[PDB]
Structure formats: structure tokens, C-alpha cells
Length: 49
Length: 49
Image (cartoon, chains in turn cyan, yellow):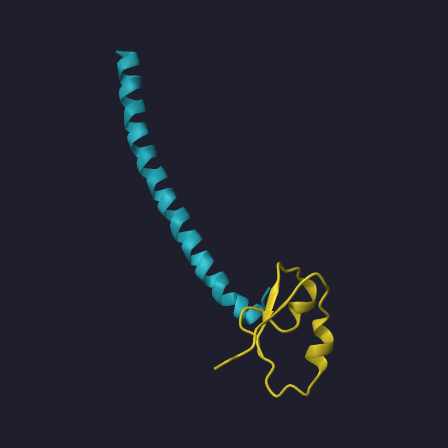
């Protein structure tokens, strides 16, 4: 639709939104990984004992 | 105040000739770059003179 310089504004907006959302998702993934790893360590201990 | 309104449909628009018509003192576009107009398909248009 648009010319590169004008498009760049919308490009910036959308990339900002998308990167912010996905890094937030990654943070939530990190937290879930931490909790599940704790669960797995407990489960391995229960196994071995 | 009594601005006329007109509807156009069921045809093909050649914006290149109009754009090349330098007689227009102001030829500006908001949602589109003036060049791209000759490569899109549209539901309909409104012209107010």
C-alpha cells in the first residue's frame, strides 16, 4: 500500500508490539520451566528413594 | 456546504494518467503512496467535487 519511509512508522509500531509480546511470553516460559524443573527434581528424588 | 457526492463502480481505474496530469495544483494522498494506486483492487470509491 505505502511508500517505504511512511510504511516504516507502522513497521516500527507493529515490531515493537510483537517483540514485546513474545519476550513476555518467553518470560512466562522461563517461569514455567523453573517450576516444572523443581517438580522434576522432586520427582527424581521420590523415584530414587 | 452543498458538496456534491458521486459513486463509481464496475470499471478499471488508470491512475497513472491522472497522476501525470500536472494541471492539479495539489495531488496528495493519505492512506496510499500516489504511485501504487495503479496496482490495487477496490470495493468501490466515492468522489466529492
